[PDB]
Length: 19
Image (tube, rainbow, N blue to C red):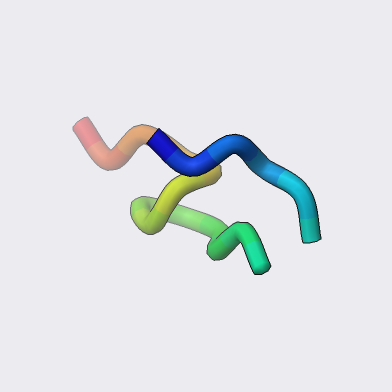
């Protein structure tokens, strides 16, 4: 779990849920 924010990476890093 990331929590969004800025620092929050995109794609399958924290934002997107790489299935």
